[PDB]
Amino acid sequence: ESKRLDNAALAAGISPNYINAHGKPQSISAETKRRLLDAMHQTPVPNVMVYTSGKKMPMVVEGSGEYSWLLTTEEGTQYKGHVTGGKAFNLPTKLPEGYHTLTLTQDDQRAHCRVIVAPKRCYEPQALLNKQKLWGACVQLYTLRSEKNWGIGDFGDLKAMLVDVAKRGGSFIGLNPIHALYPANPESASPYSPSSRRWLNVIYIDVNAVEDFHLSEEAQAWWQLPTTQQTLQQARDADWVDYSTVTALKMTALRMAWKGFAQRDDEQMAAFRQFVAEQGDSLFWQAAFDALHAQQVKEDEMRWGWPAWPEMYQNVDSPEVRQFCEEHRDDVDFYLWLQWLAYSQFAACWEISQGYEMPIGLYRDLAVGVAEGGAETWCDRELYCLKASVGAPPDILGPLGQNWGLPPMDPHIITARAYEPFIELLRANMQNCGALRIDHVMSMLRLWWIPYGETADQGAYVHYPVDDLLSILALESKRHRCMVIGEDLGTVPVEIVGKLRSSGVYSYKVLYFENDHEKTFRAPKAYPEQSMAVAATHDLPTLRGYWECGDLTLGKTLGLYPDEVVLRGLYQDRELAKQGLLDALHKYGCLPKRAGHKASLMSMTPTLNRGLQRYIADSNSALLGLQPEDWLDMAEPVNIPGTSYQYKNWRRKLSATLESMFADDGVNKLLKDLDRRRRSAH
Ligand SMILES: OC[C@H]1O[C@H](O[C@H]2[C@H](O)[C@@H](O)[C@@H](O)O[C@@H]2CO)[C@H](O)[C@@H](O)[C@@H]1O
């Protein structure tokens, strides 16, 4: 409550208000602004400048007197001239797209500026330039079943599924985030509180494709034990993923393989070592974190992250951490090996995808942040504002807000590092795939920062440099030939809708929500061309779930809808929605005349299941994502928002193996039909 404070909040990028649940402006408190400012950290040319290619590129200069300048391209090319302080000058025409370096010199000293030249648009594959309408499978990798996996779906299931998807006309397989989690705490299974967004989840390693597992005689002996084969059988046959058991199976197997691998002095060792070198420090600190984490839980299972570790292991420059790394070289190497194996197996999937000429092949998903106590915050502390957490404001459909427990990346550090952490984020998630889904793409404009320990309603939007981030996103998308899907559900200001579209970002449409206030559903053909349409997501009921009001009913049982008055409204809302959707299924040719017209009298059938998927398949959406859960007519969800211990999230497997579902007449017929819908959607 002073102008000092308000002025300070604005310069730092804290919006002074927001639109509440009731659609009214709501001002951010003095207290909130103080906490968030305290949560943040603390020239002739700026440290960085972003330009769009094909356009004029002026560089304003400050200071006094004359400067010389030197611009060096990413490719080695040099350009020079001179400039007076106070004036502006244009950089050379037709600068190629990429990362170049400008340096002004006056007498002794020099000021550096990273100069980024970006295309306007993200990459789009030719098929989509040609207005083809494509479909792919959207899977939660961990749910997959097969006759060869070890109780969790993995990279080997991913490879075998690609074939069956390609043969049926599908263009991609999309994945939940496969970001590294916590092999020392295998029950923290959430893909969305990851250790690092750069490295991978080692649990998806297919141990059957690891040659040293097969060449290790100790591994063979262990494998053939009745106690091993039993544990394995139990892990595989269970209908929920046993993360602790599957993890111990794989770590036991890979430790033994690794004893074999380590002795190698051949191509494979060289390639592993060359990978380690090329990835640099970030990879090193990931392995080190995993190795140290493994040690800490041996003392105490409840050492979930570095903030729970002794003081001496919280500071990466502490001598005790240096000592640990020194004294545990072989541990560090092993967790570096797992990352190599994860990356190589994913890369092998990618290649299969491209041998089948899949226009997208693999579709990765980038979660919106990292956990507070993982490897990323361990080794890059100043980038993250540990005194705040990213969430969402209180709204109509959640009128107490959400706190997702992730420390926000400081916007002023992103820019002070010339966008380095954002560049490296994209580099790690655009490799070996055709598309990237960016979770909560609004994050590039703003995040809801909540002061640590406070309720979501104490938060405020903190801004990020959206225009530079979009240009860099498009540049990296183009360099990787990786298209971008921006998950943009709910409230998007019209300005950002336009930016996103003109930046070639594909929008994200969920069938359930695509209806107006009277429950009139948007026609298939009025879906935006530059989008991906899906029926549901991992956060929502499956098709059967939704029709049966299973999300509402299960949710009640788990304590999520205490307020009975509101729950009555939701059930009514669903009955009205189902009716409007049924109406639209009939009206836009998705059902036979025999199908009932009154939703409340109808249960889910193979005919109705198919009609719901036909509806989105018929859409003008360039991309269509189909859940295998829906091909299998499954009722039960894989994640329930706002639960942790109350439901086994990230655990419900598919009801059938890959082998079994692609041998099934119904599944095949269904996929044949939807492939036809897409190709006839014009
Ligand atoms: O990180 C805690 C948070 O994880 C999940 O929420 C995700 C959601 O699954 C994503 O699809 C997207 O909306 O970002 C969310 C924030 O991470 C769980 O669904 C949720 O229960 C939990 O709070």
Image: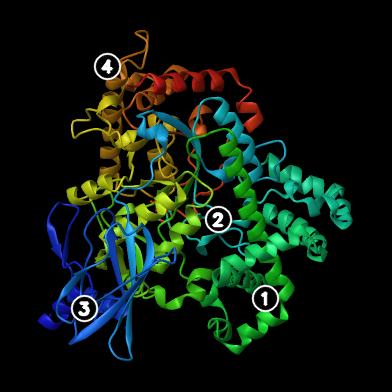
Q: Give percent across and percent down for residue 234.
A: 73, 44
Q: Nearer the viewer, mark 3 or mark 2?
A: 3
- Cα–Cα span, label 2 and label 4: 42 Å
- Cα–Cα span, label 4 and label 1: 63 Å
Which residue is at the front of the view, 365 or 236? 365
Circle 3 crowding by C-alpha within 10 Å: few under 14, some 14–19, many from 20 = some
- Looking at the rendered structure, the kind of residue marked 1 is Glu
**Residue 83: assigned label:** 3
**In the rendered structure, which disc, 2 or 1, sits on the residue that comes first in sequence?**
2
Q: At 20% from the left edge and 71% from the top edge, which residue is drawn?
A: 89
Q: Give percent across and percent down for residue 423.
A: 42, 62
Q: At 86% from the left edge and 47% from the top edge, which residue is drawn?
A: 226
Mark 2, residue position: 189
- Cα–Cα span, label 4 and label 3: 67 Å
Which residue is at the front of the view, 590 or 134? 134
Contact between marks 2 and 4 (CB within 8 A): the answer is: no
Mark 1, residue position: 299
Q: Is residue 343 above or below residue 86?
A: above
**In the rendered structure, which disc, 2 or 4, sits on the residue that comes first in sequence?**
2
Q: Nearer the viewer, mark 4 or mark 1?
A: 4
Quarter of the picture containing the C terminus is top left
- Looking at the rendered structure, the kind of residue marked 4 is Lys
- Cα–Cα span, label 2 and label 1: 21 Å
- Looking at the rendered structure, the kind of residue marked 3 is Val
Mark 4, residue position: 587
Contact between marks 2 and 1 (CB within 8 A): the answer is: no
